[PDB]
Image: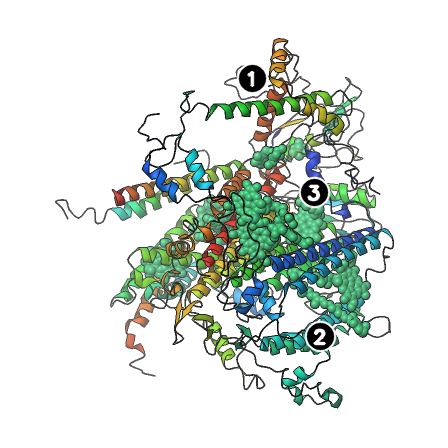
Amino acid sequence: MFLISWRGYWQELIETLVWAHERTPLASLVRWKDKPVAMSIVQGRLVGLAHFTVGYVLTYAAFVIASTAGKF
Amino acid sequence: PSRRDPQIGNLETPINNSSLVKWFINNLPAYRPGITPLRRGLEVGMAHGYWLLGPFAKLGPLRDTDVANIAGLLATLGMVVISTLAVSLYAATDPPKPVATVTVPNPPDTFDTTEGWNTFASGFLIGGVGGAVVAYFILANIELIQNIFK
Amino acid sequence: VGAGLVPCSESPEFIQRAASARNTTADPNSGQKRFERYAQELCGPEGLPHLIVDGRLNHAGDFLIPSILFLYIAGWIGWVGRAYLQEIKKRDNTELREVIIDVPTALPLMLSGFTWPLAAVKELLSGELVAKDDEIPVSPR
Amino acid sequence: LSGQTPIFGGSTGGLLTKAFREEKYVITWTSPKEQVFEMPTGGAAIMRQGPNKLELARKEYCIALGGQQLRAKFRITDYKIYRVYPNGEVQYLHPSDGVFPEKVNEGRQKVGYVDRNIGKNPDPAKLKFSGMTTYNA
Amino acid sequence: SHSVKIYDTCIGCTQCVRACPTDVLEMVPWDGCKAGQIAASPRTEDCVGCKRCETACPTDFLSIRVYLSNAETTRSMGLAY
Amino acid sequence: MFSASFLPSILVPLTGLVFPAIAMALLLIYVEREDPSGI
Amino acid sequence: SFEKWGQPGHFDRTLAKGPKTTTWIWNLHALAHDFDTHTSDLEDISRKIFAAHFGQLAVIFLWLSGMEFHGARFSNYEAWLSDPIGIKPSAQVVWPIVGQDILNADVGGGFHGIQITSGLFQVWRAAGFTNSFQLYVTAIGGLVAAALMLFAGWFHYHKRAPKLEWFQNAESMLNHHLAGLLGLGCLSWAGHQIHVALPVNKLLDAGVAPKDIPLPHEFILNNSLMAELYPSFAKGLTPFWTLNWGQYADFLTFKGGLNPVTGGLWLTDTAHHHLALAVLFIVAGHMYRTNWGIGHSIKEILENHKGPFTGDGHKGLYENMTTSWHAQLGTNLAMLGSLTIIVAHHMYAMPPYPYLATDYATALSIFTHHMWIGGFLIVGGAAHATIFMVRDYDPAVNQNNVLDRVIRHRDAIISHLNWVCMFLGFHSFGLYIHNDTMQALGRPQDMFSDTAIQLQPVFAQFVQNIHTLAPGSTAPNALEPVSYAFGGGVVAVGGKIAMMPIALGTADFMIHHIHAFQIHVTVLILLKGFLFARNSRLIPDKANLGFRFPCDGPGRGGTCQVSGWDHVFLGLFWMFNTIAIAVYHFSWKMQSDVWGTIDPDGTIAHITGGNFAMSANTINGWLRDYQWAQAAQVIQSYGSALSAYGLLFLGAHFVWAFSLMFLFSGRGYWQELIESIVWAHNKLKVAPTIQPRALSIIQGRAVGVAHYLLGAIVTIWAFFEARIISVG
Ligand SMILES: CC1=C(/C=C/C(C)=C/C=C/C(C)=C/C=C/C=C(C)/C=C/C=C(C)/C=C/C2=C(C)CCCC2(C)C)C(C)(C)CCC1
Ligand SMILES: CC1=C(C/C=C(/C)CCC[C@H](C)CCC[C@H](C)CCCC(C)C)C(=O)c2ccccc2C1=O
Ligand code: SF4
Ligand code: SF4
């Protein structure tokens, strides 16, 4: 998910989603610590790679130790 | 016919400017004038602590055990405590742009200030505890209606 | 030819497979015949033959001459392709004909690849195969 | 300046809380004809006669309208743009060259320069433990 | 915001000044080539990072470059909110 | 169990929950500090 | 007259000059049809569209006639005729050379070949087909008609081409088509049915010597055998002259159910169906205004429907529906897609051909095929909607119309949409994984099926119920319910189920809800690209710049993937997910509690054993209890005569990974590697004059997604094809 989609789509909907808090009542009290925006490009690449590598690591380890301790 | 200019990003749809709804929203304890922030906290605590114990009272992992009433009571106690903690620290770090976004025709009140927020949190704590115990009392005698049996 | 490998002639499981060896094509002798053709090599416990590559005359021709055949044909095709390319450029219709093949000229070049190896050797000794490091102007860096 | 706006019912892509508390852009021009046209915040409207006050939150929309819409279609070339402070001031970003020429003047602004060949460019070796970059000569 | 970089190869066709939608260029008087007026960046503070400008530069090894900095703000990031 | 005391029964929650709580609270109020002092 | 083909780029002025680099090749296969990108004229466009349609029809006729011909000379039809049960139809006999010799699909009677699954013989069990020579003539007719209408296209383009006002008479269009095309064809087919179909169907009850059964010429004017059955069908008694129709109760009846002697329904109902439809939409299609000064002025109807919330109603919509083409294209595509998928979702409860529910191989093949096409083309309908938005519009004729009224408040719409999607998404999936954890946590009482925490879709149950007892009161002149999955008796034949009532317990809930979930997000992506097509809150030049472009530089951070067809990229990924899990669900249920075998007591011993109530609630169960069964033979399903077809499932994974390679990588890397190889080749004087250049990022994205989809769908069809072969 992080790898394929890119930062030209995950910003249009953040606009309209900022539009909400401004105009609903009983929740417009709170405001922003800091104005939120979409991620960055390099950071997106990095997080995608991190997710991929962590996903790759775990399953194989589980498989190998479980198999070795279950078959001898 | 927008609020002040038809080109602004707001619309006069008959759900955010209906007389019924504006009357119903203005007189809420968050906005109704003639009161103190103290009472605001008291009432909000009363309400929320009065309903925020059922959602886990008979729903918790101790759902059908013979104790779950006081269990849910303790749960909502801790809940309202940590909520007060959260709002208090928010007040502690509160004053960038010391306002709230205004859409009600008038400003809500002078409730918008740090120490005001702190007093509000205190009243919230008190009212929440109160609503908790009173709901626990309503729910205490399962026979609350069985004695009436009506 | 060691490594504990039985000859495909006397490997029992080899002939065991050969008995009901599924005759592939439309001729009943297809299977059996091929198994008979597989007596020269030496089988193993798997019952199927391994190939030894050493120039050792036990299995020399079973790998050498196919290699040399491939070298023959690859040399031919590369040679005729390069020759055609070199020829095209002396027409000043370069990329017009890059997609339209000039058959009356493309034929004799193909037909004239008979003696590619030794001719290439000549172009090696004459130095007719490489341009000069700096004359070739394809800029690196 | 002007006190009138084109015919436009309304929409939801108007202003936010950033606008009336950080900045506003303003653009005006002369359209003695009233013709329907498009706007960058979604929807369409129709111009008004003579002065035409269009107020907005960003800048690029005014540039797009002036360049691609006004003089590229309807040949109006005297649209002025301004920036409005939160406390109520009125600034002046433009016309910074008067006639929107983009090439004419008798003298210009002389701010810095660099006419230096790029093959002879500094390396991270020669400029070390400084705060500058290859911009030096 | 980000930094702009000018060179000598500006022929003076002025396709970049008509391409940048951010008003960060102007042709200041020059003398060297037939241009007599070479492009430059007087108003960097509104740089956007679209760099549609050098794509409009026809010169071999296009005469303008943009060194994309790190001191971004609400202006350089371009938010309507 | 063994020769140790109750300790492994209840010493995880505070490290699990409350110490992270104060950690992040202090951290957040730190990342908003005024100038030029900060603790 | 052959001096003209080999002059490429005949339609474009730019790429007509010469192939500088390899790029010139690529665009050659890209702009060969969008001739709206060639001029501003329209009559030429329309003529091209006509000729292209004719060509498509020609290839249609060609392939259908050729498939017939294969069915006549290389298909075991006429042997499978006498026995449609103990014989499995086949075609495409294997050519006896090295490699394809063991693949002789022998289906009894020595007939080898390929055991097909497309159920054309089922049509050939209703059309009453005896000898293959008539079929030979049929193929000849099909191909000659193909060539005929192709010649017609050539003529109507090169000699006499139609004019321009010939386009926009949608009134006569609807009238002619609706009435003449549909009604006349349908009533003609019904006439064929009553004359031939049901007679030979009667004659297929007990082995009545098929070829010996007379030919239609023996019934054109021979009414004697036609008077054997149906006494009112002496001639007809022609009581229609007397307005009396009570006599015709013989054939034109209304049964409405399963006929356990045909493997399908009662064909008389279908005949009377077709009659009713024919006249009904004949009198319908006689509506609109034409050349006799009588009818609806349809451009005024839409003018009338306005009001307070409407604004100004449907004013000004015909310029869009006739001046532009992509509009019509998109809407008709969407409608066809929806229609097709309901067709798929339809013909597994009311089999309209002989031997359908009894034939458990063709069913899901047809189902999944049509279902895939449906989505696969409705997304294209939406894409053409977007291309209309970018190509065709007007600021003048679109003032305050019901169209413009949404493009002004898009943000609220899409925000609430995102809200709904988030809600449904985790409300379903996180609930699922919650139950997963509970089962893995020795807390089984926290499960969610009937044996645990409760939830029951009462609405479906009550609607099915009120459908069960329909006849008599709602349907007095009706005999049996419309289907038997709602209610009725378990209808069957042999030890083989035809249709039983379907049970909706607990597992139905989250399945339908995640269906709705994914449909919601799909609409989200597509509609988002739709509205934010011309102007975004940051990019006000989109329509000013195009809809097929990669990015707008690293401004505002990143902006890559801001066109619309990348929106439809993501959307097609999502619809892939949707339809994939949909077919998973359908196949598993209709093999778990609908299909199996039967005992003399009607005892339905289903294939799997009702596995949803047992495992279709946790994720680990979903992989175990589905693909364990869906593959446990494909590993060994090769290795004998009617097994040798080692399937390319082992093969499709490779194309899948090769696919994903294209996605994750840029292009500059490949460009530099190319330049190095060029250096080497130039050193050895073999430099190709046409300088190779790496793919453009949009090209690479396209080939990546194409290969991805191809691999996935190949994999899955291999899966269930072999799975049905293991039972069919
Ligand atoms: C779905 C599909 C399909 C199918 C199709 C179809 C099946 C169609 C149908 C069609 C049809 C079914 C048609 C028909 C038509 C007909 C018509 C249209 C008729 C008309 C008639 C008339 C016109 C008449 C005339 C006359 C006469 C004859 C005599 C005298 C009188 C008159 C003149 C009246 C296919 C496979 C392809 C593909 C896939 C899908
Ligand atoms: C491989 C690859 C390339 C390499 C670029 C090219 C053009 C490789 C194409 C090689 C040729 C054109 C493939 C030909 C396929 C045929 C099977 C080859 C047959 C040729 C002989 C039979 C004559 C990119 O440029 C690229 C760009 C952006 C994202 C991903 C990628 C990417 O994945
Ligand atoms: S940078 Fe390009 S557009 Fe600008 S002056 Fe030089 S040549 Fe002209
Ligand atoms: S990104 Fe390019 S065009 Fe835009 S302001 Fe910067 S230099 Fe000018």
Q: Nearer the viewer, residue C115 or G633?
A: C115
* Percent x, y of residue A64: 32, 41
* Percent x, y of residue F20: 34, 44
* Percent x, y of residue D109: 73, 25
Q: Are marks 2 and 3 in contact (CB under 8 Å)?
A: no
* Percent x, y of residue B128: 36, 61
**Helix, strand or loop at disc 2?**
helix
Mark 1: give few (<14), some (14-19) or many (20+) Cα within 10 Å: few
Foreground: disc 2 or disc 3? 2
In the rendered image, the quadrant that contains the N terminus of chain G is top right
Task: Name the residue type under label 3.
Answer: Ala
Q: Is residue G719 above or below residue C138?
A: below
Cβ at disc 1 under 8 Å from ligand 4: no
- Are tags 2 and 3 found on a single chain? yes
Spatial CA distance of label 2 from label 3 is: 54 Å
- Are tags 1 and 2 found on a single chain? no
Image-quadrant location for residue G241: bottom right
Task: Name the residue type under label 2.
Answer: His
Q: Nearer the viewer, residue D26 or G423?
A: G423
Spatial CA distance of label 1 from label 2 is: 97 Å
Q: Which mark is residue G217?
A: 2
Q: Chain of mark 2?
A: G
Q: Nearer the viewer, residue G672 or D72?
A: G672
Q: Is residue G398 above or below residue E3?
A: below
Q: Is residue G12 above or below residue C60?
A: below
Residue holding disc 1: D123
Q: Is residue G544 left or right of residue G373?
A: right
**Helix, strand or loop at disc 1?**
loop
Residue holding disc 3: G30
Q: Is residue E72 left or right of residue E56?
A: left
Foreground: disc 1 or disc 3? 3
